[PDB]
Image (spheres, coloured by chain):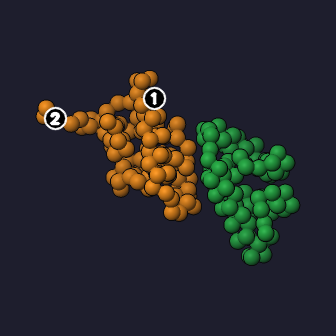
Chain colours: A orange, B green
Amino acid sequence: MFVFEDILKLDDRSIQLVLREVDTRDLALALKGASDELKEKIFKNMSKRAAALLKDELEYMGPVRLKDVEEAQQKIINIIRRLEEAGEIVIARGGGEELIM
Amino acid sequence: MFVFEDILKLDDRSIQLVLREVDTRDLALALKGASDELKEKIFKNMSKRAAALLKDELEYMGPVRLKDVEEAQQKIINIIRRLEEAGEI
């Protein structure tokens, strides 16, 4: 039941490993549908240059379709799912939730 | 009217001025709707690495939709028109 905002509960190392399997177009389309907070969490884990290429693309693109944004997000979630099986995804320090049955 | 195959008639310098303005994704989708001689013309105008960066995209992408390929070719034609009314072409 993982959704795109759950990326906020993964450690910096996981996000960096996930950023290597996505291309520039998919990472940018997904960001147009992210919280200001997930955005900074994402920019913080990219090199100085990789981030500048990203801002280039974001300015270059313009108006995009909602469904294209949702598709880019699912493609990024499937990568995470794949890297999890190879044991490379780790939940952050305070990234756990208290539940009630 | 200017269609995508008419790019086979711009010279090397003009093509280098166009490749500068287009992003990786638009070029990959666009070339997926090109003849073999238009692909060769564009490839001899981009660096050994740029063509490597393009192979990656092309392979990372997989199957694509005809509407997106058409949308990518139109973006490039729009860039070409901007460059023409300027005088840079």
Residue A82 percent coordinates (x, y): 45, 29
Query: Of callouts 2 and 1, which one flags the residue occurring earlier in the amino acid sequence?
Result: 1
Who's the residue at 86% across and 61% down the image?
A: B9
Chain containing the residue with disc 2: A
In the figure, B73 relative to B47: above or below? below
Q: Can you name the residue that lies furthest to the front here?
A: B66
Q: Amino acid at mark 1?
A: Arg
Horizontal side, residue B23 vs residue A58: left or right? right
| Location of mark 1 (residue) | A82
Query: Which of the labelled discs sits on residue A99, or is there none?
Result: 2
* Mark 2 secondary-structure assignment: loop
- In which quadrant is the N terminus of chain A drawn? top left
Residue B50 percent coordinates (x, y): 71, 46
Who's the residue at 67% across and 56% down the image?
A: B70
Horizontal side, residue A2 vs residue A30: left or right? left
Chain containing the residue with disc 1: A
Residue A99 shows in this picture: yes
Same-chain status of marks 2 and 1:
yes
Horizontal side, residue B52 vs residue A68: left or right? right
**Other-residue count near label 1 (Cα within 10 Å), few / some / many at <14 / 14–19 / ≥20:** few
Alpha carbon of mark 2 to alpha carbon of mark 1: how far? Answer: 26 Å
Residue B83 percent coordinates (x, y): 73, 70
Image label count: 2
Who's the residue at 21% across and 36% down the image?
A: A97
Location of residue B1 by image quarter = bottom right
Dots 2, 1 in contact, CB < 8 A? no
* Mark 1 secondary-structure assignment: helix
Who's the residue at 38% across and 39% down the image?
A: A12
**Other-residue count near label 2 (Cα within 10 Å), few / some / many at <14 / 14–19 / ≥20:** few
Q: Amino acid at mark 2?
A: Leu
Q: Can you name the residue that lies furthest to the left here?
A: A100
